[PDB]
């Protein structure tokens, strides 16, 4: 279960671009300021391996 | 909920944009994209129950 990938980003990444950012992503519904809630969630996951 | 029937919603405009913003239920989750992305889509019908 250690293998990480990203579900949400403000734009798609460029050729051989990379992004270390964790954050809580906000879908414009509320400025949730680094804590989860309705329409705002942590954007990294790891697989159900 | 284990044994009920379901039927198509069709030929009328999918309010998924308002359905994404609205806290109309205690939780929601999706097989395809987020509801804001579903607000850009179409189908012959959505089967529902």
Image (cartoon, coloured by chain):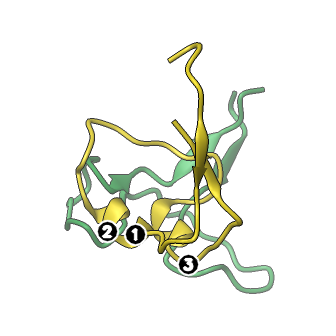
Chain colours: A green, B yellow
Q: Position of residue A41 (x, y in %)?
A: 38, 51
Which SS class for mark 1? loop
Q: Position of residue B49 (x, y in %)?
A: 51, 36
Residue B18's mark? Answer: 2
Residue A35's mark? Answer: none
Give the residue displayed 78% in from the left and 26% down from the top.
Answer: A49
Q: Position of residue B15 (x, y in %)?
A: 40, 69
Disc 3 and disc 2 in contact, CB within 8 angstroms: no
Residue B15's mark? Answer: 1
Give the residue displayed 26% in from the left and 55% down from the top.
Answer: A34
Category of crowding for the residue at label 2, using alpha-carbon neighbours closer than 10 angstroms: few (below 14), some (14–19), many (at least 20): few
Name the N-terminal-most of marks 3 and 2.
2
Residue underneath mark 3: B40
Q: Chain of mark 2?
A: B
Mark 2 or 1, closer to the camera? 1
Disc 3 and disc 1 in contact, CB within 8 angstroms: no
């Amino acid at each position: 279960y250690n293998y990480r990938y990203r579900l949400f980003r403000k734009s798609n990444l460029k050729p051989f671009e990379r992004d270390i950012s964790t954050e809580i992503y906000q879908a414009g519904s509320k400025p949730c300021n680094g804590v989860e809630g309705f329409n705002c969630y942590f954007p990294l996951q790891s697989y159900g391996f | 909920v284990y044994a009920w029937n379901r039927k198509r919603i069709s030929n009328c405009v999918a309010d998924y944009s308002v359905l994404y913003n609205s806290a109309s239920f205690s939780t929601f989750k999706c097989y395809g994209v987020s509801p804001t992305k579903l607000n850009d889509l179409c189908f012959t019908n959505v089967y529902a129950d």
